[PDB]
Image (cartoon, coloured by chain):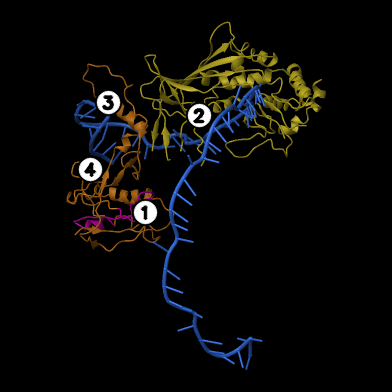
Chain colours: A yellow, B orange, C blue
Amino acid sequence: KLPTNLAYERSIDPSDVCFFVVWPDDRKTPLTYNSRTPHQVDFCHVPYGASHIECSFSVSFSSELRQPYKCNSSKVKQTLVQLVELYETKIGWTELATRYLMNICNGKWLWKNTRKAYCWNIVLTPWPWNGEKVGFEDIRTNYTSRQDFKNNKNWSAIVEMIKTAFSSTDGLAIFEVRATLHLPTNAMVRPSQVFTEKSRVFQSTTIDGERSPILGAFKTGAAIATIDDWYPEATEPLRVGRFGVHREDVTCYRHPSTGKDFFSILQQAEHYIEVLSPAQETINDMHFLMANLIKGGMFQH
Amino acid sequence: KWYYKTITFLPELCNNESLAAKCLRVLHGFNYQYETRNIGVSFPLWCDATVGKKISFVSKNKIELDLLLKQHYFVQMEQLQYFHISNTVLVPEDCTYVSFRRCQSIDKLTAAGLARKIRRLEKRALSRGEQFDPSSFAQKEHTAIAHYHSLGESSKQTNRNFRLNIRMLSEQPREGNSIFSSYGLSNSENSFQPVPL
RNA sequence: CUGAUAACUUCACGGCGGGCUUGAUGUCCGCGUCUACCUGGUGAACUGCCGAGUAGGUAG
């Protein structure tokens, strides 16, 4: 098992985020910050007189989880091809597609910029699509649980077209996303920060000539992937990794002494063909196994 | 013929801002009961990073400096020996020579302070004509601020955590025959009065 | 308690003359580097006043 060369490619493709300042006269400018001074400290705020703040990125749902990228062995080839093909039938792509979509819908990718906000609205723009712009208005007081989304006019088609994008070979689904944040006057905005191996240096880009912060493309890929609450006695959803690492406290769950990490389940691949040919925990760890093949990564020793 | 009251700031675990303010807040209660204008700033061990221990008190009428010194703070901090009284000595007339002045420019640089500013410029242009926008008001990218050793202070009347900003200027051998104010100054309405340290 | 005991090698000095390394030269043919990544400012330095002022000053 694990024959020294195995790797997958990712299946979710988020981009950078861009901050624009809309004026009352329907004019949009890029949100620019200030620097203060080696030792350098940055400061960003909403300019006075502005209505609200806009954000736009894009994400794609492709099908690179059906076969690996390099495989080195035709016994780990047809085994992992059969697992993703049997999970499509007995379980279905419903429980994963709903969890990834809600973190796009409820503004989870706005990390700490929603605290002290009056109202924010999020508009999707799917493709391929015959119909209308999809809306999610006043999300704090209208959309809070899995059921408020299921009452929507356009939830049956956007849980769909991701389910086909994982099931059909050479599939594709692309979402444009836009959000408007009604923040109070002179409110602070929190973008991503440059690493600077040992403060608060912003990750910037050039939009229309002047510099503007981004809040990252690996930063917004972490927010969508927080769907993991199958580690034992789970209280909070974590980001999908091989050893269940939590960031705020520097512990990690999912440790190999427990027997619940990825490399002690991936070795057990032949065991799970038998049951799927059971709804207690043999399901609740394939949701962790499928969310690792959608993640990517080199799997080799 | 000035005096000086050298203090000693000993106990090795102590803040340099909260104790230089509270020894000045007990000076701030003064000049609201005995309204004088004569007591200065005079840090002997000012340095660049992490200002040191000693502060002093300088005046020419030079008997209120002991009247200020017994005002329910050294009579309240006496036994657990944080500080002690100096020897009340005439200042020798050849020494180093600095000046302490409130800058107050730094306070109107922070992003809340510039929104505090362009709010005021909105209303005082009530003589009409143009219809201006707040779009053409910005701080650009670059303000290089080295060091100013801020001193935080709570307001007397209300609950505001305001702050002071005073730096070093050492020249000009003749201004200010003891024309200080409530906090001790070299900027406002009188002179740029230097200090003999 | 030494193949023991003691011990001045010195003075003087012109290497020189002369000298053509040359003629000729094709380094070439082929080529996929790639897969996966969170840096973590809670609220925090707040509100006036003079001046036409993105200059300047001034308050607690």
Secondary element type, mark 2: loop
Compared with A138, A251 (above or below) is below
Main SS type for the magenta part?
Answer: loop
* Residue located at (62% from left, 39% from top): A251
Q: Looking at the image, which residue sits at the far top?
A: A130
Q: Work out whether residue A226 can be spotted.
A: no
Q: Amino acid at mark 2?
A: Lys
Where in the figure is residue C8, as x and y percent of width and height? 49, 83
What segment is highlighted magenta in the picture?
Answer: B43-69
Report the Cα–Cα distance between label 3 and label 2. 32 Å
For label 1, the crowd category at 10 Å Cα-Cα, with few meaning under 14, some 14 to 19 and many 20 or more, is some
Identify the residue position indicated by label 4 in the image: B187
Secondary element type, mark 4: loop
Identify the residue position indicated by label 3 in the image: B121
Q: Is residue A155 left or right of residue A29?
A: right
Where in the figure is residue B115, as x and y percent of width and height? 34, 28
Identify the residue position indicated by label 2 in the image: A112
**Do marks 1 and 4 share a subunit?**
yes
For label 2, the crowd category at 10 Å Cα-Cα, with few meaning under 14, some 14 to 19 and many 20 or more, is few
Compared with A244, A208 (above or below) is above
For label 4, the crowd category at 10 Å Cα-Cα, with few meaning under 14, some 14 to 19 and many 20 or more, is some
Q: Quadrant of residue B162?
A: top left
User: Please, which chain is the residue tagged with disc 3 on?
Assistant: B
The stretch drawn in magenta includes residue B49: yes
Q: Work out whether residue B144 can be spotted.
A: yes
